Structures are given as structure tokens and as C-alpha cells.
Image (cartoon, coloured by chain):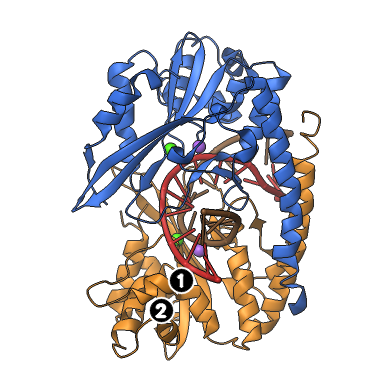
Chain colours: A blue, B orange, C brown, D red
Amino acid sequence: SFIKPIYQDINSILIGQKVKRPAAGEPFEKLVYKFLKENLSDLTFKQYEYLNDLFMKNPAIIGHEARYKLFNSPTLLFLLSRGKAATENWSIENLFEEKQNDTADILLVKDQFYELLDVKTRNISKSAFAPNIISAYKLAQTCAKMIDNKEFDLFDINYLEVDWELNGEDLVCVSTSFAELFKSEPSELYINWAAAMQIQFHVRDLDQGFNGTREEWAKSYLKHFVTQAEQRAISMIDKFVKPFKKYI
Amino acid sequence: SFIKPIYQDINSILIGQKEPFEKLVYKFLKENLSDLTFKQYEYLNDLFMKNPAIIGHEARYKLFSPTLLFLLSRGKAATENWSIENLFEEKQNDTADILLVKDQFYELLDVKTRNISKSAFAPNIISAYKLAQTCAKMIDNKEFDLFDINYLEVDWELNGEDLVCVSTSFAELFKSEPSELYINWAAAMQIQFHVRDLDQGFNGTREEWAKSYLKHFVTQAEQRAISMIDKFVKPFKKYI
DNA sequence: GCCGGTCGACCGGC
DNA sequence: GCCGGTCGACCGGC
Ligand SMILES: [Ca+2]
Ligand SMILES: [Ca+2]
Ligand code: NA
Ligand code: NA
């Protein structure tokens, strides 16, 4: 991780920062991006921003198939790329812009190594309902692709929780946490199938004791995933069929 | 519904107005149905304000109809904690956007907003699992003429330094063919559609719709459980 | 403590 | 045309 080395400063800075009032605390992310962008200038990109720079540097390379080749990495291609037509139609006059379903909020990129940062915001005033972290399914395809191409040192996926409470008509950050997906026990991750099949946790609560190799992590995760996937299918009969069979 | 009769009016005013549109819709209705229109939470304030006597949740829940209870109430603690100086507010999780109730009949109205110049990705309509519960309760409690769940679609476009409304539509969940509704299991078990494509045939009885919807739910729940195997198990066993 | 459902609407593969 | 996956958090039942 590129941001750990200065997490303490980020931590300190953000704590205190405020925001207007009507993803309620989403703009807390605009700040993280600003700070990153002030102290890691050359490494910090919004995902679309990253794609935009990528295609601007190779304006001769038009059309999606050829543009996709620019990643040199099927996995990163998978995690960062826009759709075919979207890539087909990209141009300097017609840049990529934000997209709800993009994987990362922020990319930190040095020496062709990638840290995908995602910022989970949170109202500590309100209940403590753990938020969607990332699609379990998307993460599964990610692992598959990691083995298939033997890309185990390409990239990490990390999280920065930013806690806040309401004060008057201003939202103020009271605390923050930071964690690394691939340093957690794969098998302990909670998959909420109904909740868009999303791993769910709070960053402060996430363990980091994992040992093995990145490759061992993918394998282990795929085990977990498949296992929970078999249980969920069965759970469905008990929860969504049995209770309603009688009205029929 | 209390909405359909004046759908000409609604329509007329909406087009040209410049994606928080649930606001505008609401306005017109308040200005025209003063004593029928509530935000789901406003209704709840009122129902609790007009009964200062009874307090606590058990009692308060008695004020609503296990089916309206289920669909509209805010849950034990929130309810127990309600008071004049501590009123309910907007909650993302609420079933309805707008309520319109006359003579103890309820119109749960849901405004679906749609970026008309982007893509036709049908949005979440209502959890198919919540619906299933409802249908079950309607039957168990033999209450088939109490409420409707209608939708008003509101299409919009960024033609300007603002977002403009280009068109609208209106449909009734319970005039739709059940077995036809799409249940997107991963997307929060949500029924997904555009209000404008929603079939409005169905010439059966509210009861029939329910036992038909439930059969659809169950059948679709069975497909999904199988699909999970094919999609999330078979393709990854080779790695484990 | 443990667990998992709900809103909101939004592309893109073939 | 036909399908369905994703991001965003966020509550309440026992
Ligand atoms: Ca985020
Ligand atoms: Ca709505
Ligand atoms: Na994510
Ligand atoms: Na709904």
C-alpha cells in the first residue's frame, strides 16, 4: 500500500474536516482524493481519470479491442475497464466521467503496481449496519483471473473508512480506519447474497493476520465463495419457498 | 387509485420542470389533494399525533391491519421512542415515497426516476420478498381491498444547466400480470421494470393476483437457487 | 451478538 | 430482445 506510509497524516487531516448538508457522507471522499492528490500527486487517479490518461497517451489506438490491449493484464482489465461501446466511443472531446458501479474510488499507482482504494463512509450517530464492501462474485472472478495469469504481485484492494457525525448543518469526521483486503482471512469474510452479493464489513473490525501468499489467498477465497454459494442455494428453498408453498 | 383520475393534470405540469423529482410530484399532489397526501413518515407522525393517549409500540402498532402495519410501520424501538418533540423523518428504507389515503383505503405511490438519455436499465421497483410477505398477509388476513401499490415514472434529461423532465407514466402493480414480473435476485431481490412497459392487463381478483404472485415468487426462487450453482459454483470448482 | 434484507437507480454481454 | 450484475450505505428482530 502506498498510503499506509502516510495514513497517520491522512488520519489527522481528515479528522475535523467538515462538509455541507443535504451516499450522505460521500463528499468526505472528495476530500480524501484532494489530500492524496496533494501529497501523492503522480500516483493518484480517479478510476475514470486513470482510463482517460491511459487512452490520451495512445490516441492512435482507437476501437475497444485495441484499447483493451493497453492494460497488459487481464485482471486489471477486468477490474478497471469500461464497456466495449464505451471504450469504442471514448475520445478527448468525449472523456469518461464518474460511474456509479466503478470498482475503485481512487487508484494509487507506482511502478506499475496498483492500489485500488475504496472509501467507505459511515454515520456513527446512526445504527452500525455494515456496508457493501465489494461484490463477492466480482472478487471471485478476480481471484480466478489471478491464478489463470499468475498475476499475484500486480495489485491490492484496500479500504479507508471515514467516520462522521452530524453537528448542526455540518458533517464532521470524528475518526477513520484503514485495512487491506488481501491481508484478511478469506474464509471469515461475510457474503450478503441479497445485498447485491456483497462482502460486508466495517473497516475497523477487519482482521489483518493473514499469512500465506497472494495466490493462497485467492484459492482460499474461491473455496469460501463456492461453499457459501452452495449453502445459499439451499437456504433459498427454506426461506423463500417453504414459507409460501401453502398459499399455493 | 386516487391518482389515476387526475393523471392528465399531473402529466401536464411535470413536463418542462427542471434527480430529486419526488419533490415536485409531491408538491402538485399536496396543492391538489391537500387532505390525501403524505410522505410515508408524515403519515406516521399524524397517526401518532392524533392519538396522544396510547403510547409504547404494542399499543401504537394497533393504530394501523397486519398488512399495512408490515408495509408502513417503523419498528419497535423507533416507534416506542416516538413523541411530539421527536418525530420520524425521511428513511431510505421506507416502502413508499408518497401515501394517499381516503376513507381508510391506501395508495402506496412510488416515483421511479429515470435518466432518459443514458440507458434503459430497469431500476429496482420493490423487493420481491417484501411483496411475497405482503401477499401472504393479505391472504391470511383476508384483506384484498385496502391498498394499491402504484408507480409514477418520471423520465428526465440534462438538456440545460439543469435536469429537465421529458415525460411521465403511471401504472398499478396489482393490474400487472404477476408471472410476468422480473425478479432480479442479486439486486436486492428487487422486481425491476420501467413503469411505461409494465403490463396493465390482469382481469382477476386481488386475491387471485396474490396467489399467482406467490407461485411466481416460489418458482423463481427455485430457478435462482439452481442458477447459483451453474453461475457461482461450477465455474470455480476447478480452482479450489 | 448474530445475522441478513431494503432503498436508490444504473450498463452491457451476446 | 433478453438478461442480470454493482455501486452506495444503512436496521432491526430474537
Ligand atoms: Ca466508496
Ligand atoms: Ca422511488
Ligand atoms: Na466497492
Ligand atoms: Na420500493
Residue at the spot of label 1: B109
Position of A96 compared to A16: left or right?
right
The residue shown at (34%, 84%) is B55
Q: Earlier in the sequence, mark 1 or mark 2?
A: 2
The residue shown at (52%, 30%) is A208
Instruction: Tell me whether circle 1 and circle 2 mark residues in contact (CB < 8 Å).
Output: yes
Residue at the spot of label 2: B100
Residue A6, given in percent of the width and then of the height, sits at 33, 20
Type of the residue with mark 2: Leu
Type of the residue with mark 1: Leu
Residue A147 image label: none
Q: Quadrant of residue B184?
A: bottom right
Comparing B30 with B213, the one in front is: B213
Comparing A73 with A227, the one in front is: A227
Note whether ligand 2 is within 8 Å of mark 2: no
Residue B120 vertical position relative to residue A243 in the rendered view, above or below: above
The residue shown at (62%, 72%) is B133
Task: Identify the subunit bearing mark 2.
Answer: B
Is label 2 in a helix, a strand or a loop?
Answer: strand
